[PDB]
Image 1 (cartoon, chains in turn blue, purple):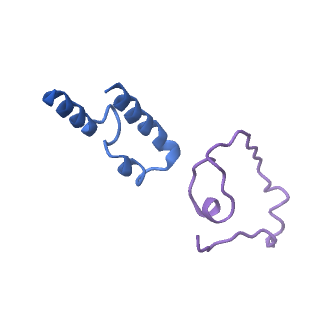
Image 2 (cartoon, rainbow over the protein chains, first blue to last red):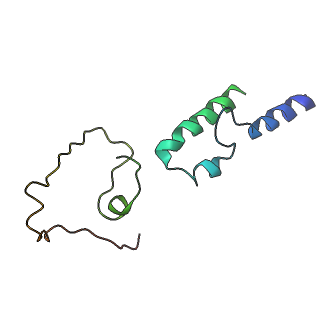
Length: 49
Length: 49
């Protein structure tokens, strides 16, 4: 058990094929119509985890 | 265009991110350019928000 959670949390700092792994970084550097794609990539990866 | 930034977009005319229409353009230099005296066309340049 103690391993599984440490695997889940450490999955938060992965990109899954995006510019960065920080939500408040993609929003502060690109306009939203260019940013929903990256946000969707992160959302799908974090759902799969 | 949706999610586009600039003087016109941030001061004169702002389109939403959920636009479901069409945009049409055609040059009007033949007539609307007037005779070195086209002055009725104006645009805002400064605004608080």
